[PDB]
Image (cartoon, coloured by chain):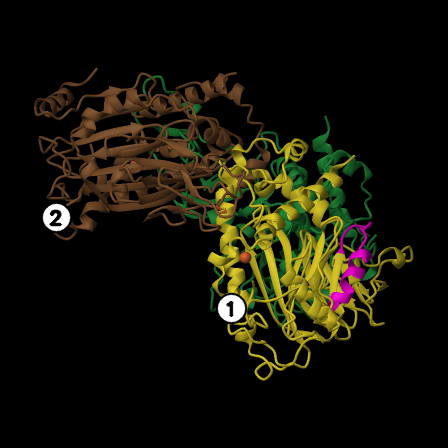
Chain colours: A green, B brown, C yellow
Amino acid sequence: NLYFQSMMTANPTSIHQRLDRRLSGFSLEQPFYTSPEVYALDLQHIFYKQWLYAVPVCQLAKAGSYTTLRVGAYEVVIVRSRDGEVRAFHNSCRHRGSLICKARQGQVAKLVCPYHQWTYELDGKLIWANDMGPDFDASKYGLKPVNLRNLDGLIYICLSDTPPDFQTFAQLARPYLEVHDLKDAKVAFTSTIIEKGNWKLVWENNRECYHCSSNHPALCRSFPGVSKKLQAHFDRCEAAGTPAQFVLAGDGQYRLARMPLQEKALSYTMDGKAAVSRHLGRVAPPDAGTLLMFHYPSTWNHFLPDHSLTFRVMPISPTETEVTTTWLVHKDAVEGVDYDLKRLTEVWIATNDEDREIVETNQQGILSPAYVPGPYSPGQESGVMQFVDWYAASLERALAP
Amino acid sequence: NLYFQSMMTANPTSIHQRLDRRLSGFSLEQPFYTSPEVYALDLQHIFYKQWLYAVPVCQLAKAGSYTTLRVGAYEVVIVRSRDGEVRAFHNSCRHRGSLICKARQGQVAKLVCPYHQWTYELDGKLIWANDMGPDFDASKYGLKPVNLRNLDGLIYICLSDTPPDFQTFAQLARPYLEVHDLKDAKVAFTSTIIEKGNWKLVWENNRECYHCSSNHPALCRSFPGVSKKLQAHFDRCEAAGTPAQFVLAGDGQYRLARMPLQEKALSYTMDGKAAVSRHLGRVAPPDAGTLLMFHYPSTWNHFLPDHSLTFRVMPISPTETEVTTTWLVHKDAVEGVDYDLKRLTEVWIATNDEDREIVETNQQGILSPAYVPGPYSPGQESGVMQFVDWYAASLERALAP
Amino acid sequence: NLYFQSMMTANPTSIHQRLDRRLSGFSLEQPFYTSPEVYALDLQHIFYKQWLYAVPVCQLAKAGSYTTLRVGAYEVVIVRSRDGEVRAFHNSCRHRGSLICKARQGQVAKLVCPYHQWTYELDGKLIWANDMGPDFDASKYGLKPVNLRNLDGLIYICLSDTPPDFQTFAQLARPYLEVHDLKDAKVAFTSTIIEKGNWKLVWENNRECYHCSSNHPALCRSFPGVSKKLQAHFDRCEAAGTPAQFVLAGDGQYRLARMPLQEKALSYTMDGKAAVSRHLGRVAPPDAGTLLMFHYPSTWNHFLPDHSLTFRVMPISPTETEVTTTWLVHKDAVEGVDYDLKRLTEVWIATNDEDREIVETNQQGILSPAYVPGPYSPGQESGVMQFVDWYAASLERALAP
Ligand code: FES
Ligand code: FES
Ligand code: FES
Ligand SMILES: [Fe+3]
Ligand SMILES: [Fe+3]
Ligand SMILES: [Fe+3]
């Protein structure tokens, strides 16, 4: 309701003027975080144009296996086709538009629409349509495809018919990710939450640890030009065949780095030790730490020697964002034997809840018409500024006539 | 929320251009089913201008008896006046605007506003107003009336001050309906549900049985130029004094036809036999089947030899529609003796729930910005096309300067 | 949902033309009570520009004590500063905008933001900010203040940087209020409710007792040029040092009058007797009755010899209004000894619920597109007209170029 109150008296969003006068050292003016007009632009120009992380490919290990997701108002279905390729389609029947797959996941022989049973093969092709006449050309009524790439076991999609370059990022990232053998994972746990903040607020909060000391007791135990200590850490990883070195995109979109953990910590556990005894991938040394990877606007990620976590950021409304956290473990690791579910997840479930509380409290103060932009900490918040620059530049380029 | 997501990035509704390029062989472009702009037009120009089925007149059998309903944002009260006429008024007090009748139904001597007790007679006339002065003319402050017609026991209303012609339809329909003696009915059961689809989607789904084979196991047992078999069926009805022949409005608004049922079925029951042993009206022969009647935009109807069902379609929002199903039986049929409530209603309660699920699943895929119009089946969906033509033509004529 | 339905087909709000043709003898045209456009104007020009009652100052009796409230989309914090002054600030951190105080009330040493711990003194001054560099000037990043006045124990605020004159009203009211010793009160009970009516509807209903006879059985027992009887009542109060005489603002904004109660009643109790045995203030005589005070747009008030009630009116949306009723009693009156909570509150809790029902029923009829303005009763509704004139004039003056 704060959102509605705030809406009423807001000055016009005059987006070009706001972008023109924006200073990189400062939080965004209110309508970036609260307005429906900027939200529609963020959808149209960011989420509907960039590559987005969807799910781990291991969720689609089986024959005829499918999983569905919403991206803004798009309903997407991702399916393992007959020929073993993974493909993605718009989950909308070409007859009258019905969703075809209604469950979050399943297995099918064919994609059969529940309304009137137009039946499609798993590559999208319409192979039967009831009583449509002889003037019906089934070749014009195949499922609409959705661009898809496999990033070394992690499925990404893009809803534009003209997607940007994914290959540069894929080629940069393979070395770092291939060593995790993600295609041999299974999902041990998924947690989906809604945060009552604009997606930008979720990213700003992710891209600093300025707030961590006070707000993240559990994570702090394990989670901490290149400094001396740090290069030394990259050197042990790389000496052992485990790529680790800081890579930052030219345009700031993604970043990869294998960072050391605090103290004697090996993993994101309350005791600091490995959560899973049967490791996912061949990372060495054991204290190689965490491979941080972000790709804007959809995902941040921690790949550890024993297990991995992917984080998917999706917009729900101007002041709501769905965060999906997926724990990946070796496909033959056994719950109750090789890992304990509580021990595996408790750290990040608590961290996520603490972040959500912070983001939500932040959003509420921002909705005040008295909110003005404020200065980011150069020492503590340069990753926030780095995110906000990427956003603003993406938006300016999409708005260019 | 899908509805909100979808809204953001939608292209302008440019209604004239959409209507201009519309082809009758195809489902509507997205904003017809999802947009608030077309929804307001549908209210203003369709629901607020056409005659609408409201309720069976038997709900108003008693002296001073009233029933209320909402039509979009209109609150209407229908009352049996002192002189035995049924009249309808705007349920808004002429003083400061309060609802007068707050319950769904009741009986009163007078209509007394609960705020300040301005008191009206049952023909709308204000007969007392407290301490209003001598410069108060009560004759200017009678309830505002609502146009009303009685279709042979079924009350219809129209919220325009200039209603279209109802008499043509009334004169066509009397022969078909008079034989059901609807004025001697009682309501044995009413079911009200909300479907999460645009009202148009509810009508398209009603006007085909393309989806029935797969989706309606219960109904299929009883529910199936003029063909040979069919004319033969009309001939037995009409030979016996029971009008049955297909009548379709010039402008496509309504339609009446007494159709045969499957197999040995006499009624909409799980066993195919009559639900009520004491029949409503004098229909013959017993296997005369069902009198189908639709009148756009508000109602479809099945009148059987033993009992009848009316269906009222009312818009709630761009993606919500209230369907009210009323089972009418002879006023002296006794629950537990002449009929069993479960046996009377189970078929259509399940059918309605199956239709609602289908409509809702259809609406969700339509909200995808990838939804495009698709071709209707000429063999299976001509009634859908016939409905969509009536809608588009109604809207084009209202938009004409 | 009525609100949404109503919205769709409404004619433009053309506010100037509506104000131009407005007649003082008549209820407002629909969009004043139902539209989001007039709601935003009411926020921007009324609620965000006038002085508003916030809370009793006794809620802030302690060192470091604070209480928070929302006014439209503003989040405000009121704090007892180190030096004993009460001050109000925008509850938004100057760093990235977070709420600082999250609870409704509490005590602090300092105002410490929960996100990153920027720490402020209780006068607003930022005294520590972590790792902001040497180019950080903390003097530019103090909390934004909110104008505040103390009306003889009752805290008022104003969100404009250029508040209107409060002193005239404060100087008129002190004599009437000082005798209640409000600074020595405590809150014995607070009740917060939401009424589903526009705030204007809540005020119109407050400003008449045209509806009371039928709708307020409990209150009627105690609640009833200057008439003879009435001047006689003011004369006993004033003879005894208790100011009582009718004072109405020049511009109609406020009004004060100590009115007599019915019968032998001394207080707002089911039995008519004093609710609290230990009196709040030094009012005499004992049957001095109730000091009525209203100040538009935020508050009406009953100050009795034994206890007092303040009523705070805040807008939530076009058809929702939060009413907060606070019972004040002497700070040393003891619950269970000097008063019984039920006996103290039952009359106004029931009255408020009856008013809310009436306002809600009124709002629903108003949402009908058939609602037209109607005539107010000159004898019974002149206070309603007096309120509506104040509103319209306030709005016209704010809209003046
Ligand atoms: S909507 Fe899919 S078969 Fe008809
Ligand atoms: S609103 Fe109906 S009598 Fe006043
Ligand atoms: S938002 Fe308050 S310290 Fe950062
Ligand atoms: Fe965090
Ligand atoms: Fe159906
Ligand atoms: Fe009242």
Q: Closest to the observer: A75 or C50?
A: C50
Q: Closest to the observer: A65 or A374?
A: A374
Residue B391 belongs to the span the image colors magenta: no
Q: Which residue is mark 1?
A: A340
Q: Residue at x 70, y 67 (%)?
A: C235
B102 vs B258, left or right, is right
Q: Is residue C72 visible?
A: yes
Q: Secondary structure at mark 1?
A: loop
Residue C394 spot, x, y in % from top left: 72, 44
Q: Secondary structure at mark 2?
A: loop
Q: Closest to the observer: C9 or B139?
A: B139
The reply to whether label 1 and label 2 mark residues of one chain is no
Binning the other alpha carbons within 10 Å of mark 2 as few (below 14), some (14 to 19) or many (20 upward) gives: some
Image quadrant assignment for residue B222: top left
Ligand 1 quadrant assignment: top left
Identify residue type, mark 1. Answer: Asp
- Residue at the limit of the structure toward the bottom, as seen here: C337
A198 vs B343, left or right, is right
Q: Are marks 1 and 2 in contact (CB under 8 Å)?
A: no
Residue A89 spot, x, y in % from top left: 48, 36
Report the disc number at residue C260: none
Residue interval drawn in magenta: C158-177
Q: Closest to the observer: C252 or B79?
A: C252
Residue C172 belongs to the span the image colors magenta: yes
Residue C183 spot, x, y in % from top left: 74, 72
Instruction: Tell me how far mark 1 sits from mark 2, CA to CA.
Output: 63 Å
Q: Nearer the viewer, mark 1 or mark 2?
A: 2
Q: Which residue is mark 2?
A: B338
Q: Chain of mark 2?
A: B
Image quadrant assignment for residue C329: bottom right
Residue B218 vertical position relative to residue A176 in the rendered view, above or below = above
